[PDB]
Image (cartoon, rainbow, N blue to C red):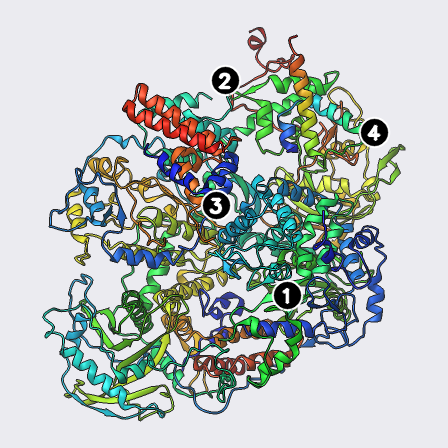
Amino acid sequence: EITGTMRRLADQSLPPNFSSLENFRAYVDGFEPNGCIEGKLSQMSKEVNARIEPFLKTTPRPLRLPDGPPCSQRSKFLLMDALKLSIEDPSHEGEGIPLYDAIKCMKTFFGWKEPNIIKPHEKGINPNYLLAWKQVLAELQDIENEEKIPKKKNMKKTSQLKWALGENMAPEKVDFEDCKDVSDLKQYDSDEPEPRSLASWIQSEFNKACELTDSSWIELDEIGEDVAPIEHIASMRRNYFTAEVSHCRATEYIMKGVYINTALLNASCAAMDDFQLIPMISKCRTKEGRRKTNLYGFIIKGRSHLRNDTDVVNFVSMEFSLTDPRLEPHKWEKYCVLEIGDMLLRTAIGQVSRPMFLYVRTNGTSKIKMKWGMEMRRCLLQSLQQIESMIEAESSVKEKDMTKEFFENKSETWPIGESPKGVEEGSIGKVCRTLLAKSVFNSLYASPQLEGFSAESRRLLLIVQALRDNLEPGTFDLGGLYEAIEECLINDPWVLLNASWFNSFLTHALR
Amino acid sequence: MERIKELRDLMSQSRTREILTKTTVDHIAIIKKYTSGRQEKNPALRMKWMMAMKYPITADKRIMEMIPERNEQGQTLWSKVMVSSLAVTWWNRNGPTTSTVHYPKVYKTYFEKVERLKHGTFGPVHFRNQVKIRRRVDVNPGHADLSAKEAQDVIMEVVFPNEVGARILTLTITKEKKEELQDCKIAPLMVAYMLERELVRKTRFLPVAGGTSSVYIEVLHLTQGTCWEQMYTPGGEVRNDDVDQSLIIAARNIVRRATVSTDPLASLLEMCHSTQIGGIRMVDILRQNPTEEQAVDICKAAMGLRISSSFSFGGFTFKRTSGSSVKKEEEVLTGNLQTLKIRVHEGYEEFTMVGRRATAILRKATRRLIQLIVSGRDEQSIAEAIIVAMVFSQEDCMIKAVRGDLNFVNRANQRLNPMHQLLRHFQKDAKVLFQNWGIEPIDNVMGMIGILPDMTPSTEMSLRGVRVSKMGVDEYSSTERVVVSIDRFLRVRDQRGNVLLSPEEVSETQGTERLTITYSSSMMWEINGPESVLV
Amino acid sequence: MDVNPTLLFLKVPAQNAISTTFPYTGDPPTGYTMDTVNRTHQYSEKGKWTTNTETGAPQLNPIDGPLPDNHEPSGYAQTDCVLEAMAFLEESHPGIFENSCLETMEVVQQTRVDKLTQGRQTYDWTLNRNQPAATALANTIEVFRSNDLTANESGRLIDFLKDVMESMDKEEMEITAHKKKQRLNKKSYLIRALTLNTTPGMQIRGFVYFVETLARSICEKLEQSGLPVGGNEKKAKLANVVRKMMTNSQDTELSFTITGDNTKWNENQNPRMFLAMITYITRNQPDWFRNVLSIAPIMFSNKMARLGKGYQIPAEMLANIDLKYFNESTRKKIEKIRPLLIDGTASLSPGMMMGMFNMLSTVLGVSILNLGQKRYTKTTYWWDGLQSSDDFALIVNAPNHEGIQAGVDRFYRTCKLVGINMSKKKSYINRTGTFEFTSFFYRYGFVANFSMELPSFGVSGINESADMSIGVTVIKNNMINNDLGPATAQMALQLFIKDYRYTYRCHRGDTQIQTRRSFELKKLWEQTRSKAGLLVSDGGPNLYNIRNLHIPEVCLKWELMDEDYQGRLCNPLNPFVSHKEIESANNAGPAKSMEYDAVATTHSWIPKRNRLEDEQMYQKCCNLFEKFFPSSSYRRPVGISSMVEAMVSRARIDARIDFESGRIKKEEFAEIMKICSTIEELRRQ
Amino acid sequence: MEDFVRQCFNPMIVELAEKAMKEYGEDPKIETNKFAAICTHLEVCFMYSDFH
């Protein structure tokens, strides 16, 4: 039954022409499927309609672009500017202690000049950074005096570092019933961000991201014997892709994010109350095949009272470089730089002695933020499959599938570049590493503006691809689609480079 | 006393006494699902951290007299009951070697697959835009086709006899299991679980690319792909693909025999109650085997079991996809001066017909055929399908194509309804209909070629509404379980008076017994050996 | 030179490699609720105001209101149009709803309360917060037992529903806190029972399940609704309908295909229209059945949205404040939302939350599709399509290139008539033969990039054997179910191999890299002659390949092991096995777990301790029962008698049998039986 | 219940249930519990009558 406090809502739940739900049930049971639809159509205005608007090859307009300050960099860690500390030390990786695997990296450089501040935060007390840096060196040299080697050094709760991490930077937690009639009781600002215009450096970073190096960076595990039908085909796909992308620099980027976030979380569990030091370690293998360990910089962790997953933890990063910030200043808005010394750089004729710099920034992360980055190897699979997809779809139309002829024919060319107002064709492996780096940067520069742009670009690209096939498409609200696209474009430089890519593609889409 | 004290000190708190009193045994499954359900904190990360830490394992206390504290290199792997991982590997090398290696008698469900891969000869990978066949097949190979309950009762008996269910009725599998592993118990719960995995059937709906048995399915991930396929023959056979065949043949011959009986229903009932198949009664097999076939469906209907709402005709099983049916009796003239009253279905309908060797989709208005899309294997199969289709068209075009008198009777010389008469007349020869149907020019689109009356493919011309599909039409075995009302003449009328099943589309090539079957009810022995008749 | 990946599409068409546009594998990282309220109540402002009679919360009833004036989205639907369309669908299918209702009656007959637990997080009003399933369920049951309301003790879910109704019938409801048994007036109880989050409340969940079950028995019998199936099946549903439209002889017919979505769809579906369609589905059906399946839509007719925390400014304090202490936007939003909320809860009449009635929404979409099979059109154009919650695909055919727009117009008009605001933005047209449908893409070919979230190739983390088999099993599943290329499966496999090796600190003994464990492994590697037969957990070579991704490692290497190796490994007399939980993976949607053989594989143990909230009630009893009868872990037991009447008798028989011929001291026996008699004397009162 | 009832009983009691329900037009599709109770009562009376 449906008694009071329940039926009272049921008879109150009916459309605005009835009184009790029992009359409603009778009215629905006895119904007239008479065809009121035609009359409702005759009553509705002619303006309420999906007037199809066409889509011809002269309709697509190139995308608009924000204008203003150049796009800075918010990447968590360095892409190309960071420098390695080659040691060639096969310590058997017996859980090779990452701190004492780094003290030798420090022991392997000479020419540590006085810390010379070059580029400040442009706002704030900068000397605290270099004070923290000299304190880092001190605690790096104050270890052997504590009678015992500690496996990790807890930085002292120092005031300059307390400001660098903002631990002391805390407001009042006051109930509203107490703070009544306050003069500065206005709301937090919470303003929406400013449109950061496009700069030219992100494309150069992406270009250098796709190149190959002399290190291997991978241990692709073994596979059982391959049987005749497919296992041989699966092999000659995956192993060729490996050898063409094994030594890619994007592999180094992925491993870098992996190790940094891994050490950060694994300490954040156990460093639950005190500061810790975070070495930005990477690993690789020489061209002669010797396990080499690289060090990129140091990172200082704040408090790790991580009760929940979205809990914010502040951290400070100091990465080595040989790239002078004085070259392009606006790129490093969140960064402060220190002239740290000089290093030897051997060439065909002696050394050049270029200066060494230290880039430092403050940022935040969380547990999920790290685990998205401990699994960044996914960017490999997404690559291979979005290669493997093309190996099947475009080869679906064949009795003997086009698989080996996808490789093994350098005459097959792929349009991938246009610097001199001309289409530049490339070979396969460049494309393979290109897609790998695409997924890599999308993963590390992950931003919701990229999500929205990808969603809105799929539609326009699909329509253009249909028009290229001469299948006479059309649209509904083209200005509205442009409006959504512009609404999902503010400051992400990776998004903006994809946008200029898209515009030049439509210009070169023969449309 | 080891156990009960927890119950007593649990009965100490009143709020526990109440729940231990009220809820009954039938409800224990409804209560074990009351858990906090919060310790799902990234099992990858917690597992990695606990592996970094020493001693994450919980052992018993009896490791003291079995393994040492110091390994052969002085490694610590105990506590004060926690144990580190290295103890496992050390015990994995050198410990109490045991002849319990007779293990591959409870895990045979895996080593069967292993052996299937051993002699599993392969073939070439002919890539192709493989089309998905919406079929329904089993998941467990070689399990004698047994239902879950009748199997888990035997399981409960063999593993926990001291608490067996109330089913005490008085199959030797009980004896074989109790004998071969009597004192060689291994891991009770895992033994019973894996036996349920070995014997219990489960059959559901998948898109396949030619795999029939279960063995062709457990290796599907090797065979099927996006645009490839690999033929792989495991070198064997199971029961589920060749046990139901014996019941199929036995019920088909039983129906073939029941017509001559005065009341075929009663003779069929006594047969089904008496006939034994593979040592198991046929009645239970019908109640428990989900096989769909005219003879089996009719035998199940005789015992009041729900089946699919099919308009079975022409050897082809039908399924209601859309549209309504209206009687609209009507007059018809033949090609030899004969009047015939027939039930011309009024209204619009749209159906999907499945056959033994072919499938097709059809749309039908009042005496109108449109969009007939067929796919078969042999020329003869598509021929039969197109023939029964044009018979079902009910157009006057096929009405003109009648040649000769229409006298086709049951094996008991009984006048058949006109539809089946036309079907059987055309089945031997129906070439005359196409030449008088009409031709239409087609456009060679979407890999759909045309067919000519001479059974020849053609490019730009075809029959009205016809389409030749590639590598199979989309099947759909709709799930319906509706009551039926069989008559005394082995006719099937579910609820609407529509003829569903009839002993006119029941026979095909000779029956070859695999399972040993025995009849015991009525005469039903003129087929079996004469010595069998005497004995 | 500068590099551009998108330029690749000049050589390869988009539908062949659209996967490159998919950036991510997973998903990347209290005020928006007000935006949702304003968005919904803007699409329904037509003076349908009625202050509630039992909640006092004003409610808009915009159904059967004015027709749409502007081209912008609108939430106005006339009742007779919707019911007429539903009856038209039934005219397309004879009494099929009563078949679906019979399956639903079977369900409501057998279904116990357990099906309330298998699901996502819920909302408990006992603590006014999101909590897991069994938490809210147990607190609700115990607060019901606090009063006379105890029908749920029968175990059938319908009795729990009667308990819910009687609970609404009672005025005072004492809430115990964990004491302080003083809270919960009647009105606030009613208000909170209708509270919604993001995510249904506690009472409605069962009911929505019923409604959703109905849709299953409906949607399984409908071809144009292919939502419940997963992945591969939908592939077929793409090619069939194509043939139903483009394969027309004498092809002067012109077939166009659009793929569209419906912007802000979910905020427009009014629960009362669902009430109407359910009622018509229950045409002349038994009364109480109409009563049960009408619960959820009526509850949604008066449903409150929770805010929770706020900005500290708790939500229940948004009533006594001036609108100057805020920004401009917040000020304007509070102005347009202030009087609608009561008791820290927002009033939302015509709403529906995304992820609640998606299958019934698919029923409505298949209805508006079914309304054009050249029998309700009386015109030349005729369409058919496939529907989802919001992203649909349609094929409209018309022989002349001028009237196709008229068919598309009829579609959009009728969709506006039923509250389907077709998104002009998220929609695109082309000629038949290539389109999108919910991350599915067709250009003469297939792609399953809907559930193409490549698996957690990391270990699942419970075991050395079960974890490996589980990983490779999910590999094979996504290889056939969520179709991916084979070499991608190879790469994911070897990645899982490395992750599993390094997770258990066991790479192998042929490489000199050393763990805290590799020494013993290398000693084993040395003393074994047949190297391949060793387990991966025991330093073995990975030979898992596509042809044997299903066979567990143990049975595959079983012949190649050494005799002592097996005789020591599979020996179940191992001291590590302790009889506790097995197989429980239960990933959130259903919960699937398929583990395989296990021998001396008991690694991942002792997860840390965390000793109303007293979970120590149910699981304790169930585990004790299991400790008495092992069968409780395999087969659903069968028995009417009480727990104690079974356990005491079993204990007495056990004492008897292991005393007479077994091994026990007579004094221990006598004490056992005296304790049992004490239990009996305690259960008698 | 219904399908199980058709499983664990003879068709003659089924026809008897048909006849007894037609006495008052009691549709089995609804009164499934009545279906079970009536078939139960009938078979109880029978096994009370056999061999007496």
Q: Which residue is mark 2?
A: B170
Image height check: is B234 above or below B251? below
Nearer the observer: mark 1 or 3; the answer is: 3
- Tell me which residue sits at (81%, 50%) in the image: A29
Please determine whether, in this image, residue B37 is positioned above or below residue C27.
Answer: above
* Circle 2 Cα neighbour tier, 10 Å, few/some/many (<14 / 14–19 / ≥20): few
Q: Which residue is mark 3?
A: B33
Query: Is the same chain shared between marks 2 and 4?
Result: yes
**Image quarter of residue A412:** bottom left
Measured Cα–Cα span from mark 4 to mark 3: 71 Å
* Marks 2 and 4, how far apart at CA: 59 Å
Q: Are marks 1 and 4 in contact (CB under 8 Å)?
A: no
Please tell me which of labels 2 and 4 falls first in the chain: 2
Q: CA distance from mark 3 to mark 2?
A: 36 Å
Residue that numbered label 4 is attached to: B405
C593 is higher (above) or lower (below) than A34: above
Q: Is residue B190 left or right of residue A486?
A: left
Q: Secondary structure at mark 3?
A: loop
- The chain letter for the residue carrying disc 3 is B
Give the Cα distance between marks 1 and 4: 65 Å
Q: Are marks 1 and 2 in contact (CB under 8 Å)?
A: no
Q: Is residue C355 left or right of residue B340?
A: left
Amino acid beneath label 2 = Thr
Q: Secondary structure at mark 4?
A: loop
Label 3 neighbour load within 10 Å: few <14, some 14-19, many 20+: some
Q: Quadrant of residue C66?
A: bottom right
Number of marks drawn: 4
Q: Is residue B508 left or right of residue A173?
A: right
Q: Quadrant of residue C201?
A: bottom right
| Residue type of the residue flagged with mark 1 | Asn
Q: Which residue is mark 1?
A: C266
Q: Position of residue B223 (x, y in %)?
A: 45, 47
